[PDB]
Image (cartoon, rainbow, N blue to C red; front, top):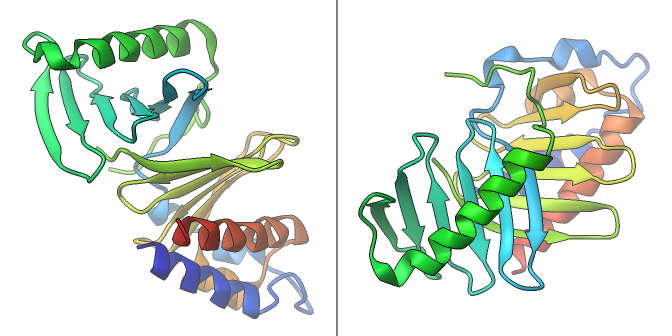
Length: 215
């Protein structure tokens, strides 16, 4: 899915989408393609444990420093443990192995923090009709998050803009400075252009996706 994403982005960036005689970004807006999942909160505690996050359906997840993941579903009981090599086990809180009690405890600590203390990104948006965090890194400018369903999210720290890239829909959601959420089909930005702000963010995305590919 990453290879596809990189190709979609390269293709948009090659068409010089901000350099058209008239840019019609609004023509590319596609509400069909609004994603199902995105990361609405996150906490990096990789100094000790890992990266905690919440997805827009209120499921919570941790990627542990040992590259394993534990996910609590929005029902508050179902878990999925994903091992370093991707192997999945389905469990519950009411009846878990004791071997996972540490990780479930940690999971509850992230859950309570995120619930007590953080704002839900895209909270006004209805997603369209569960993945885990494959990986993440932070640059000086942003945090990049790569989900197991192929989605890449990027959150830029200074201005608080976010991009959500989905290679399945070949679509991008931009959350701008005023907290407006607009979703675009990549093939139509290729046709009708976009503003320099979005075009700049997409050039950066292209770059971050080639970092994800060499790791």
